[PDB]
Amino acid sequence: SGKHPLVQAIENSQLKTDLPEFAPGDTVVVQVKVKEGDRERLQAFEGVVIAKKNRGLNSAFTVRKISSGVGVERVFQTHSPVVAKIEVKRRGDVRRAKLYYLRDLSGKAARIREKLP
RNA sequence: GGCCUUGUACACACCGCCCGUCACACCAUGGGAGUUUGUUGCACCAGAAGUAGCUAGCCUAACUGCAAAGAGGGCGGUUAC
Image (tube, rainbow, N blue to C red; front, side):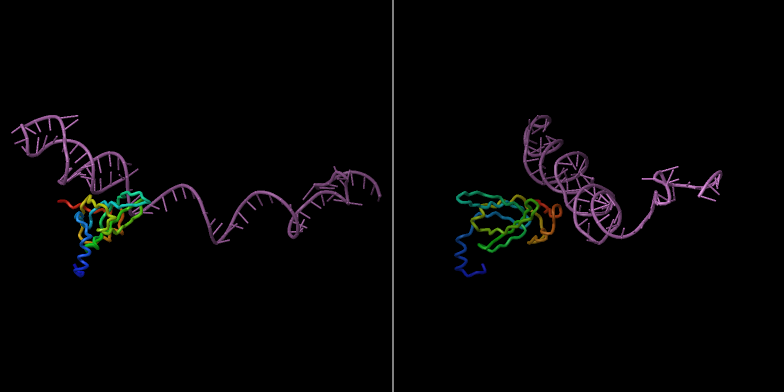
C-alpha cells in the first residue's frame, strides 16, 4: 500500500481471490493457458520457486526448471488471467528469500530439503 | 714377322668388354612446418537402469488385537558400486 488510494482502489478490483500459500524453495505446477488460432489448452510448468515479489496486483514469482538438459526460468505475474491454476507439490526448507545460488548448481548439488511438519 | 709359356671380367673375340656424374621419361619409397582419423594410459567431474546398506516422512486387503492400534508391505529420501 505504497500508492495513492485511488490507484489502490483501481488495482483492488482485479485481484485474484483464490491463490494458494507458497514460499521460495517450494516446487509448484503452474497451468498456463495456450491459445492457438481458436484452440485453447492448458500447459503445465513444474519447477522450483526461486523468487517471490509481494506487491499486490503487481505480485510475481519466478519458477526454474530443467528441460532436456537446458535450464529455463519464467517470471509469472501472479494475478494475470493467463495463470489458470497454481498447485504446490512439495514444501522446501531454505534459509533465504532469494535462491539465485541454485543457478550455479547441477543435479545432486541443487536438491532442496523437504520441510517436515 | 714366326714358335713355346703366362694373365684375362674378351668369344661379334681390344674396332672387345665396361664405370660414374649430368640431361630426358616412368615407377615405388624415405624425410618434412603442419592438417586430420581411430584407439589408448592416467587424473578429475558428472552420472541412468540395477544391486547392496540406512532411514523414519507419507500411504496401506490377507496376520495379531473387542477395538485403539501393532506386525508386515508399498511409495519417498539417502549412501556405495
